[PDB]
Amino acid sequence: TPEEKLLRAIFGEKASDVKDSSLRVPNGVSGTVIDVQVFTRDGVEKDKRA
Amino acid sequence: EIGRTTDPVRMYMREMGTVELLTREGEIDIAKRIEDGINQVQCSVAEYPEAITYLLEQYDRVEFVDPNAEELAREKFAELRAQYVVTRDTIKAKGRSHATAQEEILKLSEVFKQFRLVPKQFDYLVNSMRVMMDRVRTQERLIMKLCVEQCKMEVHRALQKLQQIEEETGLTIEQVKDINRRMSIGEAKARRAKKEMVEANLRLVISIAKKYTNRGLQFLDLIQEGNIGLMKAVDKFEYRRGYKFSTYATWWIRQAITRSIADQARTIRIPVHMIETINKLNRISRQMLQEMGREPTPEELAERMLMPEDKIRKVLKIAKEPISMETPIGDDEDSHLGDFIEDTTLELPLDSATTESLRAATHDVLAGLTAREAKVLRMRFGIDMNTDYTLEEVGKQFDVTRERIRQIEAKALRKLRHPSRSEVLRSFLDD
């Protein structure tokens, strides 16, 4: 809506086109991470971690 | 005896059981009678000359290859045109329905029958008769009613319209009625003939259908679609070929059933070709699974189908069918999948309040700015007003100069960038 146009024009926010869908700890839970496991599809390249 | 068997399948089978099969002789008998009816209607159509005129004119207007005569079309129709034209003169020669003119008409029809006509033109010709028949009947039912009820054998007053109808038609009413009723009789014979084969072969339809019934649409839908196919096949069958009827009919029945099961039976309608590809995929997977003794990886499957890997992957993901909103997800049949699904369209009361606050704050900050600067910024971004007016419109309204508006905006940005004024707007920083 127009007011964000005005705001970005004032402050020059690029406003990139991508969301934040990360995994986070459920509220209240508090612990230690003991291991991590990664499963990749056959065609996809493997990351450094994997 | 009917035990109120409400099952529609039982009613269908009970109704179809009465008609008994007959083979190798009837099919020839009924086919002969169908062809006889069609020949009768074609002959009687050829009898009517104005239909021939109209068809020839329509041919001339428009302007299809390989006619079954027991620039090819134009040169073959040139002599037919000449014959028809020279036959018109003989009809004018000393006899309206003279035996010689009738013989010429007969030979013209004999030559004409040797050609092939597109069925749509044949229907057009039939309706060209139906329209005038209905017109003449409608304009005269009132005169017949009046002569029957009042005269019992005005008269000359009503005779004017009857004479006008003859003048418009330009032909004897009696022959028109003869040809029309002959149309009706021939068509009736043809129709009543085809019913017999159709009612005879319903069992064939049943067998072919039940071969496909394994959990598709439903039994009766398959049966009815097959019956459509059977009607088509009865239309297309020729005994002259000398083959058994079933051999021909089965292809049309399978085609109809399979085409319907492709079109319907899915909520999201996959086109036909994709259905064929998925069926190939499944037929290959079974055989390849039993050969290797396990499930085939998509790469090996792609190798066998001679298709690129991505295509196979796309088909695999497209294949799946939607899941019912009432599936019981809880072990106890109390909670259903439907209660578990969230609405996405709604916004949050938090964000609504935030938007309202933002609008108020922007209005407060803008009000503190210079009047012309404030109205310019409103006019440019469409703030508070229904639409945003472009640079040219603002220039022609306030001050023609284009670059002056650019300088106004530059100064407004400079002012609102001053840290004093912007303090509250920073709170809308993360967004």
Image: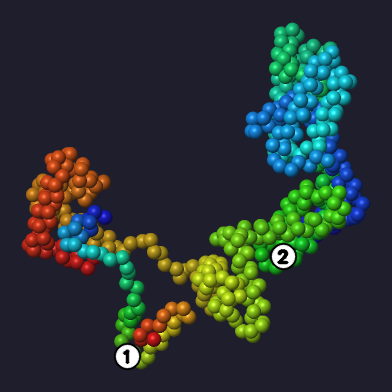
The C terminus of chain B lies in quadrant: bottom left
**Residue type indicated by callout 1:** Thr
Chain of residue at mark 2? B
Instruction: Give whichever of B343, A32 is nearer the camera.
Output: A32
> Image point 80% across, 40% down: which residue?
B69
Instruction: Give whichever of B88, B142 is nearer the camera.
Output: B88
Count of numbered marks: 2
- Side (left or right) of B411 relative to B185: left
The N terminus of chain B lies in quadrant: bottom right
Q: Which mark is residue A32?
A: 1
Q: Which mark is residue B212?
A: 2
Q: Residue B428, how many percent across, how many down?
A: 20, 64
Q: Residue B228, how many percent across, how many down?
A: 73, 52
Mark 2 vs 1: CB contact within 8 A = no
Dot 1 surroundings within 10 Å: few (below 14), some, or many (20 or more)?
A: few
Q: Please say if B100 is above or below B221.
A: above
